[PDB]
Amino acid sequence: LGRVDIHVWDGVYIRGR
């Protein structure tokens, strides 16, 4: 049921920063 944070953020992982 729990997770260790998601890679992507706000839909897609922003490039660089």
Image (cartoon, rainbow, N blue to C red):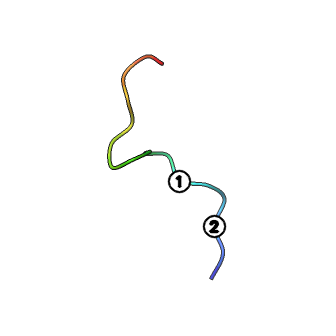
Distance from the alpha carbon under mark 1 to that under mark 2: 8 Å
| Residue kind at label 1, given as amino acid type | Ile
Identify residue type, mark 2: Arg
Q: Are marks 1 and 2 in contact (CB under 8 Å)?
A: yes
Instruction: Check disc 1: other Cα within 10 Å, few if <14, some if 14-19, many if 20+.
Output: few
Q: From this viewpoint, which residue is outermost toward the left?
A: 12
Q: Is residue 1 above or below residue 6?
A: below
To which residue does mark 2 refer? 3
Q: Position of residue 11 (x, y in %)?
A: 33, 49
Label 2, residues with CA under 10 Å away: few <14, some 14-19, many ≥20: few
Q: Which quadrant of the view contains residue 16? A: top left
Single out the residue that lies furthest toward the front: 10
Number of numbered discs overlaid on the protein picture = 2
Q: Which residue is identified by label 1?
A: 6
> 3 above or below 6?
below
Residue at left offset 36%, top offset 22%: 15
Residue 16: mark: none
State the image coordinates of residue 6 (x, y, percent, origin top left).
Answer: 53, 53
